[PDB]
Amino acid sequence: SHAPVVFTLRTGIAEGRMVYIGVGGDIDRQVNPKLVVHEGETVQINLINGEGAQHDAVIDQYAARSAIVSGKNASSTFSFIASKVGQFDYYCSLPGHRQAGMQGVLQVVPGNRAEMPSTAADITRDPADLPGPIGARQAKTVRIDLETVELKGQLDDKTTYTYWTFNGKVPGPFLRVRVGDTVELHLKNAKDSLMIHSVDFHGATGPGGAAAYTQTDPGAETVVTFKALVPGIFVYHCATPSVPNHITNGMYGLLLVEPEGGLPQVDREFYVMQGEIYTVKPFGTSGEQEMDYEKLISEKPEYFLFNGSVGALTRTHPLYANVGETVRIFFGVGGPNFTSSFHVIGEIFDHVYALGSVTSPPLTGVQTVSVPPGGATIVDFKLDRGGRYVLVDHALSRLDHGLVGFLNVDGPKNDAIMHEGPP
Amino acid sequence: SHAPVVFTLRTGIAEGRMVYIGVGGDIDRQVNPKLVVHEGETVQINLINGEGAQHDAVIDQYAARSAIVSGKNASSTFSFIASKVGQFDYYCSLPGHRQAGMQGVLQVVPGNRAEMPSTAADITRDPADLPGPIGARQAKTVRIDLETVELKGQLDDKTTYTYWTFNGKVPGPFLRVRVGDTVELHLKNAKDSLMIHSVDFHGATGPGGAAAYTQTDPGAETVVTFKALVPGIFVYHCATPSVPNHITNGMYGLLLVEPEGGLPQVDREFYVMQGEIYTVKPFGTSGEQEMDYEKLISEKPEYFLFNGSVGALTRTHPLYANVGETVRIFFGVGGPNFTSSFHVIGEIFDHVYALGSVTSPPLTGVQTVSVPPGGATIVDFKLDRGGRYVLVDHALSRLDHGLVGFLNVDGPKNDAIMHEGPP
Amino acid sequence: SHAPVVFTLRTGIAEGRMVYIGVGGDIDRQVNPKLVVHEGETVQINLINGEGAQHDAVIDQYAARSAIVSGKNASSTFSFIASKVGQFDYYCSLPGHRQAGMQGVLQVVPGNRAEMPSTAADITRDPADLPGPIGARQAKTVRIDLETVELKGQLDDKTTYTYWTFNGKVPGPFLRVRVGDTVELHLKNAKDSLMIHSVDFHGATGPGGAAAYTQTDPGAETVVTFKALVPGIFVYHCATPSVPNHITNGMYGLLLVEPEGGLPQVDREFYVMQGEIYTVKPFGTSGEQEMDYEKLISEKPEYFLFNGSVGALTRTHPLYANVGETVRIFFGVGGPNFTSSFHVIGEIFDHVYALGSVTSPPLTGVQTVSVPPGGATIVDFKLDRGGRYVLVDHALSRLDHGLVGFLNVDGPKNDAIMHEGPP
Ligand SMILES: O=N[O-]
Ligand SMILES: O=N[O-]
Ligand SMILES: [Cu+2]
Ligand SMILES: [Cu+2]
Ligand SMILES: [Cu+2]
Ligand SMILES: [Cu+2]
Ligand SMILES: [Cu+2]
Ligand SMILES: [Cu+2]
Ligand SMILES: [Cu+2]
Ligand SMILES: [Cu+2]
Ligand SMILES: [Cu+2]
């Protein structure tokens, strides 16, 4: 699995004993916590040395253990599949440590993990929620309506956040026009907004990429007109100070200006954007999460996200396709600060529109592409066979801050292209 | 304005009251500070929860307010245009907090902010200070003279730093030759230098890119000859240990090696380089700033700068051009550590010379290009209309460490490419 | 030299006197430590102000000195060539400070520094250790054997670390097949492994890029068959959770799928991968280094390495080539988290295979290329002349965490391409 269930234990002294102490999640600060797991789940346990004696963790029945960690902060992660139901001791095997208190239970329960009923609006943009290709057609005047909306959203299972959005979702509406078009932009800022909002389009030519004409008071509306002079895949974002603050809170999206021919036909298109959120409390903390200004200006986020939320493209709104389809992903980074090393595990990019150029010839046969903040690209590939394909930033520590996504494709396990055993 | 006046407030207990406390700038550690602002200026207020009670900041006559912030370190920023002259109360709206002492005054003064008289040397290279296109001509021997100079310089309004430079400015002189040219380089280390200085040209072939031949004692001169074998836009930099130290202090420049044809004809060329400075005290602290080794080797800078200084390309040496003109920016990253997401707000790159290749086809219709430390690129675009165009690193938290520049182009606010109402 | 001997001194109060205190390496916590150096070494001294009085460091016989550091954490670094054998005082020139105790000895000893005798296995891959170009030949079944081995490795001179590897070295085996080939992969997990291991190939099509078929218990074997459908230079890595943990401990390599025509003829090929290691104690600490989870998940490493170790490509297994040879470097980033700015000091890349595409035309005349984690590229250049050419990540603070390599080429100092003095 690429969604392991994760527990963090720090060694320490508590309740008059030498113990394991739970760190974050549902086990924060509990001593020798019960690790509750569902049958068939992959379990990851991170052991961190708290007080500076030698330690490990061992679960006899799964032939699983950490390495021995010796000094303060020394760490060892191990994993296994929870294949047998029942109750199992995790313990420290160092002389005396089990007797002295270093012992807890892993409970493997039958059936599938139930999802926590949500407490706030779903702010996640479905990756299929974009307009299809524009027909061949003359250049013309297009009216676009955006509303800036401030609202609490479901950031994770049991954690909320005050998002700022275009039309109550992250990313914002996928905008699709043809080069030469005249865009009539209307920006309504909701009555219940505390902040002024605006929009800079990277596909617009003139002051602030429209920001100078879109500074909108709450309950007010701006109207601006601009020509789409250049074909490309452009990120748009709020441009009201603090711009980094407006971007982290959710105010980014993509503007496709099709070239005259349109893009090469493909069977299926998807909308994906990466960003960071900068919270006071670390990744995995339950409750209302709040923004930490010191962490934002110092570029030290706690969440890395596809389309606004943890589980956005795994649990709530994943990608779906059929064997033999050509797939296109519009992938942009709102940021505000981090470059994505975009990759799909189990696939290779047939075409990569380098630096989001739609007019230059695409690069071919590419594993991984750098996309900067305030940049996008286009990738396509043919699905030659079935699987769960995984979208990642290949700076892979971002898996542990919520950045993973699923492309689900129905096919047999084994075939000519990849199979168990020899040829 | 894309240069808002920024104030940071931490809530706390001080002078026997529950108060706002100034953080950085002119208001550092003052309780309930007076925020002084000039008519028309954009004002940004950063509120940070200090002691852990619920707080906001409210200014009534501007219908401006932070969000409510609950736990320690929780934060909200808000902004507005200081369109109204006089004195206005900023205060906390939570039951009792204003009575308990959470109140200060915003003073809006008529007229424009006067410039601070400078303590130290202007070390900013004018972006228009470069030699123009070489004619067509035969390859030949070219003499180049560099001087390595240690001098105190104006990092910011009230703040100085010890710069290490090529010829007293940052970046160093723009060197321009043709492929085939034999370069006769004279490097003179000034008598009053403490340090050995040198140079490595990324456009030279041989040991240390000339560094092995140019290790120059203070008060001495070395001479080195090298052939420009490959066309490109190259960074040069000091190559005396510690090389990161000599770079952060400002010893970086660009060398253009023109291809046979020369580069395409353009109306106007500009010289811009990005670097970092690693100071003991945070961004905005007045006085002599000093270098912090721990922050240098761990890649934690306080300043992100175009051409040496805060306000380099906004206040003291901004960029000027006329509507209808095609513009080329030679953009390099001295670094020493951070990759730039280079972008011009309100413009699109007609051409981007990928990884600084002068011989491969440029990519077309690009919003944003990654440039690594020790790398450079060329961008160009036609100025279809007038406005303030803004050079940024689209890692936009670097806005709050000094990274912003202006390209000023005279023209009407409203026109066919972007305008106020509908069509 | 581009590998200086480095000493850090913090000023403070110890043993009843105002003194210098050693930081890190052989001098950690020693007062006025003896700085022992071999004749001809380049010496870098980092002064850090500890207690807040004014300090410098002066060595009279070498005309060498720091600048004056005033505030706590204020830093100045200086360098010189230890050209003179004997004992030289380093001392603070501020009034009284020398008399108050700020004085130590620099000892310069004749002859070269002996290498320290290792304690653990050599785990660095020789950059020359790769199979050469495959003939022209028909597509066929190729069998590959990989063994996952956990073992202590010589990380630095007197520091060790528990590495996880493919076949006992970092990077893993260079895999070379022809496009159209069928790969029969055998992965054996050694009996003495604590952990499950696996492999994902970025050049395989299907679930986990083979990870879904290769989750192998200790003392077990897995077998998977897959078709090489795309030509490219692909990273492969372990894909057992924690994937970031498995990668940082050393489980990455390169798979070249040759195109039918082969890569261009070249005189000499090399294998180089860049990674990070996240240790509890800082770079330079002797003894057993252990893994720091908190540093891994927050992207804050202590070691930046080519091919597994400090000195990997300078002392133990450097690169050798001859003047006039065309050279190819296959360069990959295992990571797990940092984008490399790959540069060879003294050279310029004739060709850069952008995003590791082997089917799109290579870019020409490039100084420096961004390679993401889980990305790879090919550079080639002609060696016109002799020198030590230096492999670096141009994020040059990484010089101070172990990231440097040597390409040694026998030839004269002075020729027509680069010489001392004028024409
Ligand atoms: O295979 N990439 O995580
Ligand atoms: O050439 N720079 O390391
Ligand atoms: Cu124990
Ligand atoms: Cu906004
Ligand atoms: Cu932008
Ligand atoms: Cu209050
Ligand atoms: Cu220098
Ligand atoms: Cu360099
Ligand atoms: Cu002193
Ligand atoms: Cu592994
Ligand atoms: Cu991968």
Image (spheres, coloured by chain):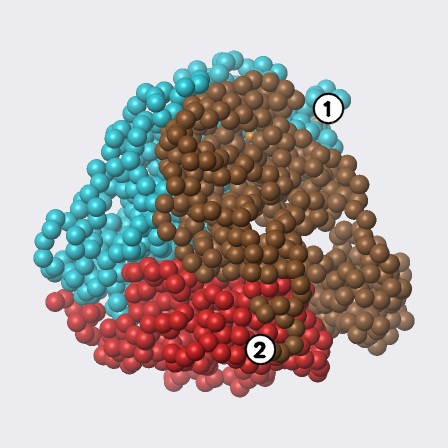
Chain colours: A cyan, B red, C brown
Q: Which residue is mark 2?
A: B184
Residue C117 visible (yes or no): yes
Q: Which sits in the foreground, A99 or C83?
A: C83
Residue B7 visible (yes or no): no
> On screen, C330 above or below B55?
above
Where residue A39 sits in the image (x, y, percent)? 45, 18
Q: Please rate how many residues cluster around mark 1, counting C-alpha atoms within 10 Å: few if below 14, some from 14 to 19, many from 20.
A: some
- Residue visible at 76% across and 43% down? C158
Q: Which sits in the foreground, A323 or C288?
A: A323
> On screen, B99 above or below A17?
below
Q: CA distance from mark 2 to mark 1?
A: 69 Å
Q: Which sits in the foreground, C60 or A115?
A: C60
Q: Amino acid at mark 2?
A: Glu
For discs 2 and 1, the disc positioned in front in the rendered view = 2
Q: Are marks 2 and 1 on the same chain?
A: no
Relative to A63, C49 lies left or right: right
Q: Which residue is mark 1?
A: A94
Q: Amino acid at mark 1?
A: Leu
